[PDB]
């Protein structure tokens, strides 16, 4: 077995904890969160499993010292500027790290000095760090890249992830601009209340893996404007109002389009015959056209991949790794 | 640049050679085949493009000094074991497309232990790969389970075109036989259909930590109504164009893995649609289709080529696809 600690016990951290508890060769050993409502409570009671004898620690360093995990999963924040010190904190204790921070999936191009720092500390303490997740971490990077494994040569990549926002509450409705008018949408993008984090990371992982240079990435966030009435538990989109945000990205080299990613997120796509799914098109020799229907669920997949990568991160060479350096993902035995 | 040798210059070996020649980070250095028609000829002339075909594999490796030899000879461990071991004793790495070499640890543990031991003694590595087994019904399925919390059952289908492969495969699938001859050949063991189901099953099972105690197989002939002529074979009407091979793996009467692999030469002559389909029943459920199918020739050539650097770079021993980093296309 491998011993695991958790640093953020939110939607993802808690799902991950529960998933760890299901695995035959993993052991959940401690959890830390900075929310007053969780500190000192039993993790099993917080997950609805009754008491398991694992308390939420007030301090991450105390958690690692007292329980001795081989690896800590950090599910706190998206940004390198915030998570760098969290990761480095754990590496200084000679433990491995998986994070789902979207920027940590491939940080070498966005923030080279921070990536170099993490990699150096990781090496000094003989341990490894990986950033992963469903997106970035699997569907628009790892899966595409693996698919090119049976190509003789690749000219262009086009991929899309279409999801349904219906299940989520107001917090997500506001982040995707759902229920807004077009003017309110445009003000929301300027203000930062309204898309997707990770396109730059996915692009650069694909490029690194294929040996391509990328010199330009263009991004666009456009309102998906409903022609029909869409009503969930938490929102009512009238015709002409916004049902979600369409975040697209295009990566170029010298005016050649190489990679093209799209991820429209809307409430109730099926009301206009938009099919949820993941779709990958490799143009090359040969051409490949893959569809997964419906889409790999974002919460479940992230919980799954962060858990499933644990043994290979513990076992890997020291340093800042990426999904492209590690063996193929697999479901761990329950 | 990684220097490569080839042992087996058939449909796949030759395509692999040509693919190696296209790559920035590889270099083709020698080729050996046992066909009189090839020996001493230039490999570039044979492909329609200063590398001679050697009569002896050991002489080829000694005289040209590859880091790795690709073996595209035969399907069976009982035949290729000595070919692989022959190259490892020269301190070189090996990739083979032998279907049995994709995952030999459960079918033939003592042969796998022998290859692994010799590989370790000489500080080099061996991998078995290919489109199938090696990617579509093992590596790809397994990767997909990477986003599952738990997996109950796997069902997958590969509708395939046999056109790209040479006489060795044509004979193993009973192509160009009469239907009665095909059915007698499956019973007698002269025709076996698709080789690799057992290997794919055990790779999936090992990766997920499942035990398999029973594998049932069924092989039926696909009878052509039309004339089908490929580079290597001619199927007259009423003759067999391929084999419909299915396999089911169980644990205690619970079906865990189900594979369908209908294979024929030139399916499109009778409007047979190809493709690769995967259904994972679990939490969550996953349902993937690739349409048309990953071409069998191109994908095999591709994957055997693309895995070269990672096999050279790997830890010593008998590896499998599940031990190595993710497959990717090498730059041309
Ligand atoms: N890689 C991916 O594809 C992917 C997918 C899902 C989520 N994510 C990212 O992961 C995080 C989401 O996790 P979530 O959905 O559970 O979020 P969340 O907001 O529900 O959970 C965050 C939890 O961590 C706690 N936390 C935050 N900062 C902390 C700190 N410094 N110390 C201790 N606890 C701290 C919060 O209080 C909360 O309990 C976000 O950064 C999200 O962007 C990425
Ligand atoms: N794993 C996969 O997905 C996959 C796919 C395609 C083929 N294969 C296997 O790879 C092998 C090659 O198939 P192919 O279509 O290229 O066949 P082929 O008949 O076209 O070529 C085989 C070649 O090997 C040569 N050869 C055979 N035995 C030899 C020996 N002992 N020493 C030297 N040369 C020898 C033959 O003369 C010929 O050139 C077969 O066994 C086939 O089943 C695997």
Image: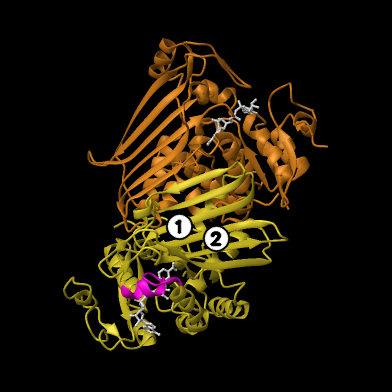
Chain colours: A yellow, B orange
Around disc 1, counting alpha carbons within 10 Å, would you say few (fewer than 14), some (14 to 19), or many (20 or more)?
Answer: many
At 48% from the left and 25% from the top, the residue drawn is: B271
Disc 2 sits on a residue from what chain? A
How many numbered marks does the figure carry?
Answer: 2
Chain of the residue where label 1 is placed in the rendered structure: A
Secondary structure of residue under mark 1: strand
Rendered position, B259 above or below A95 = above
Residue picked out by circle 2:
A324
The image position of residue B282, as x and y in percent, is 30, 51
Tell which of B108 and B139 is nearer to you.
Answer: B139
Residue that label 1 marks: A161
Question: CB of mark 1 within 8 Å of CB of mark 2?
Answer: no
**Quarter of the picture for ligand 2?**
top right
Asked if one can make out residue A318 in the rendered structure from this viewpoint, the answer is: no
Is A329 magenta? The answer is no
Q: Is residue A231 above or below residue B197?
A: below
Q: Is residue B207 visible?
A: yes
Tell which circle, 1 or 2, labels the residue nearer the N-terminal end: 1
Q: Which residues are magenta?
A: A170-182
Q: Is residue A228 left or right of residue B136?
A: left
Same subunit: marks 1 and 2:
yes
Instruction: Report whether B273 appears left or right of A145.
Output: left
The mark lying in front, picked from 1 and 2, is 1
Relative horizontal placement of residue A201, taking residue A178 as reference (left or right): right
Instruction: Please tell me how crowded label 2 is: few (under 14), some (14-19), or many (20+) other residues with Cα within 10 Å.
Output: many
Location of residue B199 by image quarter:
top left
């Amino acid at each position: 077995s491998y011993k695991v600690g958790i640093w953020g016990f939110g939607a993802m951290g808690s799902g991950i904890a529960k998933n760890i508890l299901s695995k035959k060769n993993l052991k959940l050993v401690g959890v830390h969160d900075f929310r007053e409502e969780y500190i000192e409570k039993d993790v099993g009671e917080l997950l609805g499993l009754g008491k398991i004898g694992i308390k939420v620690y007030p301090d991450p360093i105390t958690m690692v010292k007292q329980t001795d995990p081989d690896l800590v999963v950090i599910a706190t924040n998206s940004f390198i500027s915030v998570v760098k010190d969290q990761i480095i904190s754990i590496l200084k204790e000679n433990k491995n790290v998986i994070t789902i921070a979207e920027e940590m999936a491939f940080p070498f191009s966005k923030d080279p000095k921070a990536a170099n720092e993490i990699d150096t500390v990781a090496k000094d303490h003989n341990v490894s760090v990986l950033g992963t997740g469903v997106n970035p971490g699997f569907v628009l990077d790892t899966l595409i890249i693996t698919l090119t494994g049976i190509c003789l040569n690749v000219q262009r990549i086009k991929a899309a992830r279409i999801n349904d926002l219906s299940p989520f509450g107001p917090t997500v409705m506001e982040t995707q601009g759902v229920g807004t008018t077009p003017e309110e949408f445009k003000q929301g993008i300027k203000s930062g209340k309204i898309g997707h984090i990770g396109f730059e990371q996915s692009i650069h992982m694909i490029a690194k893996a294929l040996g391509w240079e990328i010199d330009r990435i263009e991004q666009k966030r456009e309102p998906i404007i409903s022609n029909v009435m869409r009503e969930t538990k938490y929102v009512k989109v009238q015709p002409g109002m916004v049902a979600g945000c369409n975040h697209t990205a295009k990566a170029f080299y010298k005016n050649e389009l190489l990679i093209e990613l799209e991820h429209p997120q809307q409430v109730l796509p099926h009301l206009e015959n938009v099919q949820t799914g993941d779709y990958i098109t490799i143009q090359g020799d040969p051409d490949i056209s893959m569809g997964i229907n419906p889409e790999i669920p974002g919460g479940k997949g992230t919980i799954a991949i962060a858990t499933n990568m644990i043994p290979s991160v513990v076992e890997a060479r020291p340093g800042l790794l990426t999904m492209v350096d590690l063996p193929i993902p697999r479901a761990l035995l329950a």
